[PDB]
Image (tube, coloured by chain):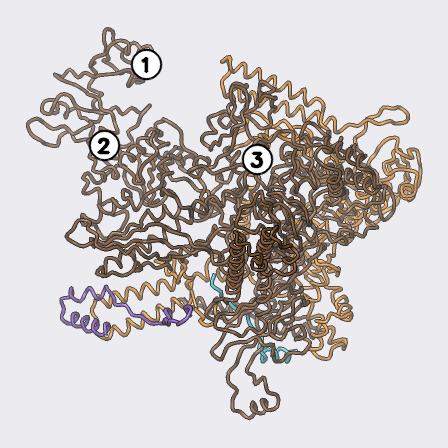
Chain colours: A orange, B brown, C purple, D cyan
């Protein structure tokens, strides 16, 4: 491996050999000349040192190259360590048929599918393209086939679309911690440069659609293709192999859509309408009623598998809403209606999927997951569902609670000045009263957010659950929680941890009304602590996993 | 009233309530002030080269009576300019030459000098010179040297106790850190014994270091301990007890005092008893004999008659020994006190542990530690011990070290010596014992009063000193050997060692790295970076968990936001806006003095230590007109615990709200409404933005963009300018007015802009003029706009019209939906420039040549090549076309009839040459911007190399003749004026010069002499012009010197325009990033009631979970600003009168609370309003300070002025169905920026390529079409699936199974899909490597 | 070419060089055996030549 | 790190053998 071409300058494997060879030659030609004992013993000592350094450098002494203080890599150093032979032999090998790209979302896709760019394809499948071209008689010779593939002709594109058809390809997220980091899909050729991934499998892959990349590997033997179809297919990884809960569950922008479409509000357009159930979609789409209409009576034909291996119908006239009546179209046969006739949060649809899998089987539950994703995505967009400054409201009692807490703090400080209370007791009381004030503020803020006032049946007074965007999202569980809302409308709370302790004065402000320089500087210790904790615990978790796998 | 003629074009509205007191500093002082003082001629030798020389320059021969000194050093003038260095590839530096003095003196005379050789100076190396931007041009590439943050030399009493002790006991050690030399550590053991440790090696007993300093047991005892008299005469056995001095111990029995007994037997000691014993004079009181057995003797007592060693020092008294020592030795015996409660010996227990009692046996112990063998011979051990610590030229810590040492030991004096001292050692040990017993507090390493910063100049000085101390040895040797000579002072002064040391430091170092070049913000924040790693401090990113936290003393000194979020989080920081460096290197920050309630304008800089005493108020505190406080109770910081204080306790107040944030985090609008994590991420992602074609200002800013753009040095600012004469796409010339003009110059300032040059990141750097002809320009006004700058403001991104709503799942998690209009209008389009080079590399067969006579190639390939063989400028090249036609000679053609026939038939090829041409790498396409060719001296091929030469020569002639033309015109005007009223009209002078007819008037007055003098001056000017032109031509055509092998170099640059597409990564300023998932046609994109479609659709499900209310506030403010701009645009389109437009602009400028006074119709004329309105017609620029921004009420009010809904929401319609969305949506204008992670550089695919010679595996990470890495976790996944066949396939067929790869390829092409696994090659390599050791290994059957 | 009348230098890296060994040069006198002394003397002579 | 394990190149004989295999 020459550097400048003129001189090869072999290093780190031939320097030690050269040292040993020349020193041994000198000792051998000095041994037969009746050399003095001191000289011959000294030469033997240097020969011993040279051989020891060749076999292992770091153990005794150090041998270094010119202009670099780094030692040489002896024979053993290329066996042990993370840069040794085994850890490149232990599947540390690179692979031939592989490709990368940035991950992109494709919502039109179904569970057993992915979007593979045409530029990336026709390169991973090039031997197959050559084989098909030779078989169909479009290129009598390998050179002609190569030229035709290099020119990228329409026949080449048709042949690629033909050969890629029934051929699974498997994707792999870079940190693969459990089994589901590798799944096999059916490639669909897209015009672009980014791999399109399925939102449902994003949760298993732990992908986040911000610069994440994904590797592609092609199985070519028949056993490998059948294996990717029958063991690694993403339509076979329904349940988690760790605990047993389903690994596919709508999580975001679908939970919100289903929650919005299945909700009840009084005095909506078309309250008293009675219909058959197919008519709810015709009534929402054209005119007449809103998907939030109440007291709507629709006749639902349930199917229950009461008989052994056979299901029978049952027709009723249960009251429901237009949105639930529409979603009943998506819901399959064997499932009942009580699982739909509700507000349908996130755990509700997770239970829906679990019941569908347990009762019907695998194919109905896969189809149900796909249809749920489609309908949730559609209605979330159709709902508008924006966010604004006025969306998060601050309770009016916050000022009075802050004033009362400050007054009690002043009273405690006066008592401490009087000498009746010592420092630790005063600190504990201050913390207790501030925590109580924080809890009261949070309770008042939730009180304001939860309840809304509306007019029903000309009564002019009604209290039904609000339609605030932040409250709706938190309640549905799509994204966020009441604890995180507390920091947007209520107070930040104590938010104090220099190393372990707690500052007596808490942050009394939220992000809607801004923050002070002192408060914002105080609130950075926890952020830095958490970021450092993640960045220096990832490696420890990886090492624990490695030891577990090696021992078991 | 602010004129600011460059700013008067477009005034940015400010929402700043607080009044600014201190203006933002230079923002790049830390990088260039240190280097300026590094090479500054100082009359007194304190820092720089003057201090580096005076250290070890006086050379004294080994009793040779011949010395060497120096007079002064002078810095040479640089050979090339910065632009010349960058275009060439050489380093920017300046030669160093110092006048020396070698004096030889004769023998037998005390200091009798006979000859001096102080007549010639020697050049010793070149110092790389710093440019105007705090950056170096080392080897043609711009590099920045980061400052370091390490622990200041001194003494630190750290605790190092807790769980690491593993005994439930606290320890107290002490370390003395010098700036140079060895370290000294004084630990403690759970046995309450102290040990001395050097260089963190094996420990030693406590008092060996004391005994080495000619100290005996008696002095050590009397110095460390206090000895009581213990006067026991005539068997009285009485004790001189002082209750004030010693007390707190219960009396056992037989205790008496003056008058009544002090304490009854068996009674607890009481404060009343102590007070009574102190009030009454207490003489020597008797105690039982039990108190003697436990007590130890202070000194060694000797009997009066004989001198036996009875009662040895540090020995407990015995009852039997007591009688004989009282009878023979003496009566009063010196003893100790040794009370556990408030004291502890901790040394007398160690004295018996010492194996050595004499200094003789003690001195060799340190030698035994230092060197294992070779015992000393009474000349080595003493010399080593004296040279280790107490030598001047081997320890020499610092002035800072001595200052910290004296401050930590309560010493008034600050001026000390770099040598340690015995008394210093005893003080250190005494204070260690004091802190162990309880006398003070342990130190804190994270405290910014214990850590100092090292800038580039001082590390350069240290490296130069290290390089000079090496050549000093050679000079001394050459002066000692063969001293009988009178040669010039170059006996051993070799510049190569010093130059090699300085080049090694500057070029290849950990703290010297390529500067970021994709943003002015990125550059200006790389130059202010502070790192803890490097040659010192923290050796690795590991070994730290509380070092990387936000210490409370980081308030106005380092930023708690800007830091990377990777492995080195917390080890990389950025200075705040106002943070300055102390005299010794610590960090300061400015405050305003508060005197008896009022707040003065004066500014005091306080370091970390000083700020801990005074009570500093808060910047967000109300202020009266006179400087008084509104509220009696104000929030302040006292010692790290902020609380409330009255107005009579405060002493200082902060300067501005931007004081705690760096320059990166001060560009984020509404920073106080964002979480710390998201603010950190937004600040970190702002630096990665890549500039686009058309720069667009932000409608929502903070006011720091102007300062950042000006101070980044990326624009072209006008120095001493008055008016513009000629404006061009690449040249600006300014006619400086006479007010700012000094005699002796033409009066023309010329600026040559930088057009389309490659950056470090392969981006584009382009400057565009802003001024027009005849536009008056003041001093400090910008003239050009660098990358991502708009009229002198930092503009990195575009104002996109965002909408917050889910859209069919195309913005699912962090994906973005972008309208097609964004792609059509060429927003976010980016220009990228690459560098390709080829060398000739002459051979023994013959030199290689670029002649375009390339064999085995078609005429189509050589269509784009010139006669010389290199591409035409402007040609488009894709894939694998030829750029430079190079041929390598082969061996001589053989006499063989076959080759003879081939030569006779074809000729001109003879297989003499081989096609080793430079071709474009696969998947690279672009158009050639310009080429550059370099030919070494002595080679005059120059096929077409003269064209660039002539272009440069003509440009130099054009830019050099202008000043001469101006001077000649002035002289001609002077002649025409002095011939007035002399009978000669100006018509003759205008027609022909004629040297004013050679004074045809012949008045014999001063006129003739005046004409002669003017003719002489004109001749001198012409001669100067010719000399300058010849000098420029000689500097231009002189030729380059390259590497010995290299014969010539040709470089080719290609420019590529990259557009937006799915996969590309966008971002905001609030830590929100994303990947484009779709480019939606304009028809489908949601539209409002006026038919205008939004540009970008974003997911509203990130705001409540990431706490980014800054996004929402920014969109509302941007919507208000765009509404104002739209109203102004409509009024301009209606061609309305000036009065109404001016009144509307004034009403829009005066809106809000009391912030800033600015009024039209009194400074702006009728015309300036037109250009102001035409500039701010695409939106009203708004500036909200960091923590003093606009309020929600003011935003709602501003929305009302542009006739917009104050709620911020608006009804939208679906573009595909025309059905109105319920729950009205939020639209606005967010500043979106495009990051440097493009999908064009991310995709890679491979089927079969080139493997490595060893292990036969695919290469790697796109290194020439490499493969991808299956790993241990991936094989674990496959095994968990049970994928035996896929695993075997990935193991063998796709990898080093050499005989199986070809078989699988053949079977795939034939349509078989079958595998022949075989055996991997890496296992064979492993077997061979194991057998290369004496270990037999094989496979059985 | 130093601005006319080029001066010639040898190749520093390519040129060979030999250095006497101090350890063995400082043990010929100490050795009390005539064989060792004569051996060291002869080898010193040959090396210096 | 010192550069080692260079790439394998495709000479004429190897290319012709590759084409013979197919």
What residue do we see at 38% from left, 36% from top? B156
User: Do marks 3 and 2 share a chain?
Assistant: yes
User: In the figure, is residue B405 to the left or right of B695?
Assistant: left
> Which disc number belongs to residue B780?
none
What residue do we see at 29% from left, 57% from top? B475
Query: Mark 1 falls within which chain?
Result: B
Mark 1 to mark 2 CA distance (whole Å): 35 Å
Tag 3 near tag 2, CB within 8 Å = no
- Near-viewer residue (A132 or B701): B701
What residue do we see at 31% from left, 44% from top? B395
- Where in the figure is residue B997, as x and y percent of width and height? 59, 60
Circle 3 residue: B23
- Where in the figure is residue B601, as x and y percent of width and height? 54, 27
Q: Residues within 10 Å of mark 1 (few under 14, many from 20)?
A: some
Of the numbered discs 3 and 2, the one sitting upstream in the chain is 3
Tag 3 near tag 1, CB within 8 Å = no
Query: Mark 3 falls within which chain?
Result: B
User: In the figure, is residue B784 to the left or right of B1023?
Assistant: right
Query: Mark 2 falls within which chain?
Result: B
Q: Residues within 10 Å of mark 3 (few under 14, many from 20)?
A: few
Res. A89 visible in picture? no
Circle 2 residue: B220
For the N terminus of chain B, which image quadrant?
top right
User: In the figure, is residue A333 to the left or right of B856?
Assistant: right
**Quarter of image, res A263:** top right
* Disc 1 versus disc 2: nearer the observer: 2
User: Do marks 3 and 1 share a chain?
Assistant: yes
- Near-viewer residue (B731 or B1017): B1017
């Amino acid at each position: 491996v020459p550097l400048d071409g003129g001189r090869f300058a072999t290093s780190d494997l031939n320097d030690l050999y050269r040292r040993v060879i020349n020193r041994n030659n000198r000792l051998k030609r000095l041994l037969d000349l009746a050399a003095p004992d001191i000289i011959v013993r000294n030469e033997k000592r240097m020969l011993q040192e040279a051989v020891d350094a060749l076999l292992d450098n770091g153990r005794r002494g150090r041998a270094i190259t010119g202009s670099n203080k780094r030692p040489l890599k002896s024979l053993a150093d290329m066996i042990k360590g993370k840069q040794g032979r085994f850890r490149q032999n232990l599947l540390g090998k690179r692979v031939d048929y592989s490709g990368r790209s940035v991950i992109t979302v494709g919502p039109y896709l179904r569970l057993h599918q992915c979007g593979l760019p045409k530029k990336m394809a026709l390169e991973l499948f090039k031997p197959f393209i050559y084989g098909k071209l030779e078989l169909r008689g479009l290129a009598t010779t390998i050179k002609a086939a190569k030229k035709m593939v290099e020119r990228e002709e329409a026949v080449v594109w048709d042949i690629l679309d033909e050969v890629i058809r029934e051929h699974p390809v498997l994707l792999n997220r870079a940190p693969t911690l459990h089994r589901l980091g590798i799944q096999a899909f059916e490639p669909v050729l897209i015009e672009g440069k980014a791999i399109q991934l399925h939102p449902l499998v994003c949760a298993a892959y732990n992908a986040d659609f911000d610069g994440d990349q994904m590797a592609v590997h092609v199985p070519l033997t028949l056993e490998a293709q059948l294996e990717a179809r029958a063991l690694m297919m993403s339509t076979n990884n329904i349940l988690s192999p760790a605990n047993g809960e389903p690994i596919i569950v709508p999580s975001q922008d679908v939970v919100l859509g289903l929650y919005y479409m299945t909700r009840d509000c009084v005095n909506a357009k078309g309250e008293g309408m009675v219909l058959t159930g197919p008519k709810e979609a015709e009534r929402l789409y054209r005119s007449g009623l809103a998907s939030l209409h109440a007291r709507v009576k629709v006749r639902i034909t349930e199917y229950e598998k009461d008989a052994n291996g056979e299901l029978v119908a049952k027709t009723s006239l249960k009251d429901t809403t237009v949105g639930r009546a529409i979603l009943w179209m998506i819901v399959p046969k064997g499932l009942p209606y009580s699982i739909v006739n509700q507000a349908l949060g996130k755990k509700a649809i997770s239970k829906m999927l679990n019941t569908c899998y347990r009762i019907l089987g695998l194919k109905p539950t896969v189809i149900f997951a796909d249809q749920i994703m489609y309908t949730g995505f559609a209605y979330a967009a159709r709902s508008g569902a924006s966010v604004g400054i006025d969306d998060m409201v601050i309770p009016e009692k916050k000022h009075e609670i802050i004033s009362e807490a400050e007054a009690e703090v002043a009273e405690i400080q006066e008592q401490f000045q009087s000498g009746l209370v010592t420092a630790g007791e005063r600190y504990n009381k201050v913390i207790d009263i501030w925590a109580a004030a924080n809890d009261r503020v949070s309770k008042a803020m939730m009180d304001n957010l939860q309840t809304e006032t509306v007019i029903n049946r000309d009564g002019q007074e009604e209290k039904q659950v609000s339609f605030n965007s932040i409250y709706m999202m938190a309640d549905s569980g799509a994204r966020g929680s009441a604890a995180q809302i507390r920091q947007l409308a209520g107070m930040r709370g104590l938010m104090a941890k220099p190393d372990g302790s707690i500052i007596e004065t808490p942050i009394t402000a939220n992000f809607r009304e801004g923050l002070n320089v002192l408060q914002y500087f105080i609130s950075t210790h926890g952020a830095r602590k958490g970021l450092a904790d993640t960045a220096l615990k990832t490696a420890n978790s990886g090492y624990l996993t490695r030891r577990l796998v090696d021992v078991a | 009233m602010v004129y600011s003629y460059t700013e008067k074009k477009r005034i940015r509205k400010d929402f700043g309530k607080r009044p600014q007191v201190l203006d933002v500093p230079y923002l790049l002082s830390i990088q260039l002030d240190s280097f300026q003082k590094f090479i500054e001629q100082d009359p007194e030798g304190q820092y720089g080269l003057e201090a580096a020389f005076r250290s070890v320059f006086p050379i004294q021969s080994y009793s040779g009576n011949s010395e060497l000194q120096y007079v002064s050093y002078r810095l040479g003038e640089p050979v090339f300019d910065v632009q010349e260095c960058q275009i060439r590839g050489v380093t920017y530096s300046a030669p160093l030459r110092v006048k020396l003095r070698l004096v030889i003196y004769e023998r037998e005379a005390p200091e009798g000098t006979v000859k001096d050789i102080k007549e010639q100076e020697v050049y010793m190396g070149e110092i790389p010179l710093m440019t105007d931007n705090g950056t170096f041009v080392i080897n043609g590439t711009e590099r920045v040297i980061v400052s370091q943050l390490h622990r200041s030399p001194g003494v630190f009493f750290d605790s190092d106790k807790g769980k690491t002790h593993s005994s439930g006991k606290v320890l107290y050690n002490a370390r003395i850190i010098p700036y140079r030399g060895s370290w000294l550590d004084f630990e403690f053991d759970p046995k309450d014994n102290l040990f001395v440790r050097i260089d963190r090696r094996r420990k030693l007993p406590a008092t060996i270091i004391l005994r080495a300093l000619n100290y005996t047991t008696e002095q050590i005892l009397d110095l460390f301990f206090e000895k009581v008299i213990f006067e026991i005469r005539d068997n009285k056995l009485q004790m001189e007890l002082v209750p004030e001095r010693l007390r707190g111990e219960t009396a056992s029995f037989d205790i008496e005092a003056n008058g009544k007994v002090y304490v009854e037997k068996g009674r607890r000691i009481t404060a009343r008893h102590i007070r009574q014993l102190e009030k009454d004079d207490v003489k020597l009181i008797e105690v039982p004999v039990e108190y003697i057995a436990g007590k130890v003797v202070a000194k060694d007592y000797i009997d009066e008659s004989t001198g036996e060693l009875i009662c040895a020092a540090n020995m407990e008294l015995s009852l039997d020994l007591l009688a004989k020592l009282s009878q023979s030795g003496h009566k009063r015996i010196e003893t100790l006190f040794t009370n556990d409660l408030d004291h502890g010996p901790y040394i007398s227990e160690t004295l018996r542990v010492d194996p050595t009692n004499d200094r003789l046996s003690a001195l060799v112990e340190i030698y035994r530690m230092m060197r294992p063998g070779e015992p000393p011979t009474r000349e080595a051990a003493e010399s080593l011990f004296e040279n280790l610590f107490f030598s001047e030229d081997r320890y020499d810590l610092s002035a800072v070290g001595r200052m910290k040492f004296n401050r930590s030991l309560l010493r008034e004096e600050i001026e000390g010596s770099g040598i340690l001292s015995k008394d210093d050692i005893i003080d250190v040990m005494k204070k260690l014992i004091d802190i162990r017993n309880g006398k003070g507090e342990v130190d804190d390493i994270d405290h910014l009063g214990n850590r100092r910063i090292r800038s580039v100049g001082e590390m350069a000085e240290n490296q130069f000193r290290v390089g000079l101390v090496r050549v000093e040895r050679a000079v001394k040797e050459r002066l000692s050997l063969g001293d009988l000579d009178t040669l010039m002072p170059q006996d051993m002064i070799n510049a190569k060692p010093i130059s090699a040391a300085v080049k090694e430091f500057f070029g290849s170092s950990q703290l010297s790295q390529f500067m970021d070049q994709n943003n002015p913000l990125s550059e200006i924040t790389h130059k202010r970076r502070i790192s803890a790693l490097g040659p010192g401090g923290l050796t690795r990113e590991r070994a730290g968990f509380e070092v990387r936290d936000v210490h409370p003393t980081h308030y106005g000194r380092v930023c708690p936001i800007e830091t990377p979020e990777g492995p080195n989080i917390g080890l990389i920081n950025s200075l705040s806006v106002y943070a300055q460096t102390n005299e010794y290197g610590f960090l300061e920050t400015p405050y305003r003095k508060v005197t008896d309630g009022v707040v003065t304008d004066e500014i005091h800089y306080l370091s970390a230590i000083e700020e801990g005493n005074y009570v500093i108020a808060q910047a967000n505190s109300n202020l009266d007109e006179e400087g008084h406080f509104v509220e009696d109770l104000v929030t302040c910081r006292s010692k790290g615990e902020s609380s409330l204080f009255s107005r009579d306790q405060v002493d200082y107040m902060d300067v501005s709200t931007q004081q705690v944030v760096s320059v990166g985090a001060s560009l984020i609008p509404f920073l106080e409404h964002d979480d710390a994590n998201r603010a950190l991420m937004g600040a970190n992602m702002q630096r990665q933005a890549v500039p686009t074609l058309r720069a667009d200002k932000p409608l929502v800013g903070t006011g720091m963009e102007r300062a950042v753009a000006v101070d980044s040095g990326v624009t072209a600012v006008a120095k001493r300018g008055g008016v513009v004469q000629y404006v061009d796409a690449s040249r600006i010339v300014i006619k400086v007015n006479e007010d700012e003009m000094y005699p002796g110059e033409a009066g023309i300032d010329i600026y040559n802009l930088t057009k389309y040059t490659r950056s470090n990141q392969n981006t584009c750097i382009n400057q565009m003029p802003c001024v027009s002809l005849g536009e008056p320009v003041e001093r400090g006004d910008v003239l050009a706009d660098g990358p991502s700058t708009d009229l002198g403001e930092l503009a990195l991104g575009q104002n996109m019209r965002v909408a917050f709503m889910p859209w069919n799942g195309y913005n699912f998690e962090d994906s973005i939906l972008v309208s097609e209009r964004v792609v059509q209008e060429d927003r976010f389009t980016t220009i990228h420039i690459q560098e390709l080079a080829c060398v000739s590399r002459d051979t023994k067969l013959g030199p290689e040549e670029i002649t375009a006579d390339i064999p085995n190639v078609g005429e189509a390939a050589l269509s784009k090549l010139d006669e010389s063989g290199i591409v035409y400028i402007g040609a488009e090249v894709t894939g694998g076309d030829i750029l430079v036609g190079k041929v390598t000679p082969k061996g001589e053609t053989q006499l063989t009839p076959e080759e003879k026939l081939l030569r006779a038939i074809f000729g001109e090829k003879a297989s003499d040459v081989k096609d080793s041409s430079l071709r474009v790498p696969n998947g690279v396409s672009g158009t050639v911007i310009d080429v550059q060719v370099f030919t070494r001296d002595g080679v005059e091929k120059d096929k077409r190399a003269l064209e660039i030469e002539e272009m440069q020569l003509k440009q130099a002639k054009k830019d050099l003749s202008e000043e001469l033309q101006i001077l000649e015109a002035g002289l001609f005007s002077r002649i025409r004026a002095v011939l007035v009223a002399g009978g000669v009209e100006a018509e003759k002078l205008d027609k022909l010069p004629r040297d004013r007819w050679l004074e045809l008037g012949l008045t014999d007055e001063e006129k003739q002499n005046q004409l002669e003098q003017l003719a002489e001056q004109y001749d001198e000017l012409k001669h100067e012009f010719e000399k300058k032109l010849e000098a420029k031509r000689r500097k231009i055509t002189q030729g380059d010197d390259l590497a010995p092998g290299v014969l010539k170099i040709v470089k080719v640059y290609l420019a590529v325009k990259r557009r937006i597409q799915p996969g590309d990564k966008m971002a905001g300023r609030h830590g929100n990033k994303g990947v484009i998932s779709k480019i939606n046609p304009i028809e489908d994109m949601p539209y409002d009631e006026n038919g205008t479609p939004v540009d970008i659709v974003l997911n509203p499900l990130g705001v409540p979970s990431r706490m980014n209310i800054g996004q929402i506030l920014e969109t509302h403010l941007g919507m208000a600003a765009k509404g104002i701009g739209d109203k102004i645009n409509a009024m301009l389109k209606q061609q309305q009168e000036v009065a109404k437009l001016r009144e509307f602009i004034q009403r829009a400028y005066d809106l809000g609370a009391d912030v800033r006074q600015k009024v039209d119709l009194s400074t702006f004329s009728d015309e300036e309003v037109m250009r102001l309105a035409e500039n701010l017609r695409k939106g009203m620029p708004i500036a909200t300070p960091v923590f003093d921004g606009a309020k929600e009420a003011e935003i709602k009010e501003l929305l009302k002025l542009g006739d917009l809904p104050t709620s911020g929401q608006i009804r939208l319609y679906d573009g595909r169905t025309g059905e109105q969305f319920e729950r009205p949506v939020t639209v606005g204008y967010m500043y979106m920026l495009k990051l440097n992670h493009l999908v064009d550089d991310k995709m890679h695919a491979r089927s079969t390529g080139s493997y490595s010679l060893v292990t036969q595996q695919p290469l790697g990470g796109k290194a020439q079409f490499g493969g991808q890495r299956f790993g241990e976790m991936e094989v674990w996944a496959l095994e968990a699936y049970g994928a035996a066949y896929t695993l075997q396939e990935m193991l063998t067929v796709k990898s080093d199974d050499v005989n199986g790869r070809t078989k699988m390829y053949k079977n795939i092409v034939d349509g078989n899909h079958q595998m022949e696994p075989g055996m991997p090659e890496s296992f064979n390599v492993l077997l061979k490597e194991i057998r290369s050791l004496g270990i037999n290994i094989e496979l059985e059957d | 070419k130093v601005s006319g009348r080029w001066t010639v230098e040898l190749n520093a890296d390519s040129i060979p060089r030999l250095k006497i060994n101090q350890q063995y040069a400082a043990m010929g006198n100490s050795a009390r055996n005539d064989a060792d002394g004569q051996f060291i003397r002869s080898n010193l002579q040959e090396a210096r030549w | 790190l010192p550069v080692y394990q260079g790439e394998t190149t495709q000479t004429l004989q190897d290319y012709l053998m590759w084409q013979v295999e197919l």
